[PDB]
Amino acid sequence: EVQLQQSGPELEKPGASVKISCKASGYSITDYNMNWVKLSNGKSLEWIGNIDPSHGGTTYNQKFKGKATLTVDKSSSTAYMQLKSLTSEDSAVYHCARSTLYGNSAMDCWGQGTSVTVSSASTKGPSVFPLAPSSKSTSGGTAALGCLVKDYFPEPVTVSWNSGALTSGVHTFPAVLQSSGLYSLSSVVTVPSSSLGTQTYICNVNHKPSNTKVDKKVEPK
Amino acid sequence: FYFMFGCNNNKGEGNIGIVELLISKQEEKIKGCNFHESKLDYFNENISSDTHECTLHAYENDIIGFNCLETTHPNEVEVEVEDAEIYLQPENCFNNVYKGLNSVDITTILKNAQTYNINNKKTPTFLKIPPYNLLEDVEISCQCTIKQVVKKIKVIITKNDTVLLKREVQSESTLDDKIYKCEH
Amino acid sequence: SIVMTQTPKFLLVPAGDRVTITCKASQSVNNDVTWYQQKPGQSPKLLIYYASNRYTGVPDRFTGSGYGTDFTFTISTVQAEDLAVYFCQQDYSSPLTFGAGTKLELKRTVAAPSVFIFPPSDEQLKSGTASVVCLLNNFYPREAKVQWKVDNALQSGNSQESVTEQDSKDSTYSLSSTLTLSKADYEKHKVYACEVTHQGLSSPVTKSFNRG
């Protein structure tokens, strides 16, 4: 029905500037008010500001005024938000939302969210390693197998099995931040032991900041 | 008030320029909402502190007011005190007005509106309604934060296809030292 | 500005039972309040607008009530997929303020974990690092403690833990423990074991392997 498309994550130096974009489809951009919402640490929503493309008027929340700039492009039906002098407090996931122009301002449609990270450590690519349940006491019942993602920065990292197949029984754990400033993640999947010798399990790991794509097979040893 | 000023060029053997100006009162009442404790004699609607919203009906050639700061009455000693940090949204109230959540300039609602502000005072702000073709009942609003409390003013801009035929106001006479007197 | 207070911060309810979330304002807002619901890894979704009206397509089990200063959000029958965090929002005067948020959880019965351990891979050993990963699944409650032993010697300060978001398939927790050791230190020992203690276990559960 209505789709809101945002850009991928950013990784800028301290004091830098970003200009994220929000593409709207399925409706006329001038027919609905659109605003941004900030997610402090992913557990507290915060209203930043809104822009009305019908007249170009802009309203900013007071502690975000000046620090952020809002603009719209009616020809492309895409709207942009700019941040000035990024600080560690600005590291959060920003969502685009759609609301009515006049009257109510309930936010009806939300995008997938753009993550802005203020670089505290250098960029690095993940190291994918296999986790073989075998070579041990026994693989009783179903055999749980997975992969280890270590020393990557910044978040996020996407892990999929068999190019999106075998969705059930997949456990992807949240990333852990080490003293070196590099994230580590582990994803596991539970499969019957009888398929250990007659089935191929492959994990797909994608890291957009480093453009790293790894397809690692997991086999018993 | 009756005065002059101008330029004098007598020393350079030139002519002399004089401007004659007079100022007279037009109307005694302004349909505005005063959310402050200090009442205004020329504001039609003074709103008690218990009430946080005020609604007005507007029409052509009418003046709308909006005050959220103190006013110096003759009983008060005038002193040089900085204006309080009044949180007014938008920063300008009536040139750009809230039509909900988005800010829109007043000229988009009213055809070439005339707005008056004070350079040395954040509030009040005034608007004189110009002749306009927007016959619809449009809603515009401002807001102020007085003592961590948000005050909102609502203005109903209307221009009916037929103006009200009559407006009859009835008042009862009052006795003032054995004399029948009527207000207004 | 107007500030929302939303209680209780953490709310627990069994599946199929009614649950109510409260909200309090600082000043009269008439009827300009909205409610949002958000899954992990997903954007928030609007459920109630005007504080008492369901939005288009919202299931009938979601309802809201309240006017002026006290507002309540109620779910008639909670489902297994209703695990989410709920927020309230005022739409009276700018800036629009969101509530602190309230997290809804399901109880379920107590279940014991099943323990697996994974040996370091040959590829990682080529880089001079050895990592041992322990996997725990479908356990309740969340307070599961993990200890690592190398040749019956307790290890500390070199392990990390990570817990998931209680995947809605069965509303149970999973935990993964990773032990990081250098390749030189790894070659100095034979037996590597991990000890797991949990409320559902009458005794500690030990898994071990021999590689070296």
Image (cartoon, coloured by chain):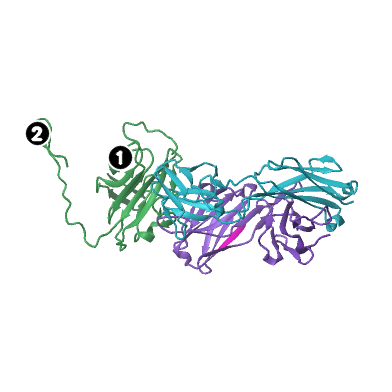
Colour-to-chain, purple? A
Dot placed on the residue nearer the N-terminal end, 2 or 1: 1
Image quadrant containing the N terminus of chain B = top left
Residue C31, image x, y percentages: 39, 49
Give the residue drawn at x 76%, y 66%.
A200
Q: Nearer the viewer, residue A195 or B63?
A: A195
Q: Which residues are magenta?
A: A17-22
| Residue corresponding to mark 2 | B179
Q: Chain of mark 1?
A: B
Tell me the CA gap for discs 2 and 1: 30 Å
Displayed quadrant of residue A143: bottom right
Left or right: C172 as drawn, with respect to C150:
left
Colour-to-chain, green? B
Left or right: A196 as drawn, with respect to C128:
left
Q: Nearer the viewer, residue A23 or C69?
A: C69
Residue A197, image x, y percentages: 79, 65
Residues at marks 2 and 1, common chain? Answer: yes
Q: Colour of chain C?
A: cyan
| Residue corresponding to mark 1 | B40
Give the residue drawn at x 32%, y 48%.
B55
Tell me the tag on residue B148.
Answer: none
Q: Is residue A50 above or below residue A202?
A: above
Residue C85, image x, y percentages: 55, 49
Residue A78, image x, y percentages: 54, 65
Residue C1 visible to the viewer: no
Q: Main secondary structure of the magenta part?
A: strand
Q: Which amino acid, mark 1?
A: Leu
Name the element at disc 1: loop
> Callout 1: 10 Å neighbours few (<14), some, many (20+)?
some
Image quadrant containing the C terminus of chain B = top left
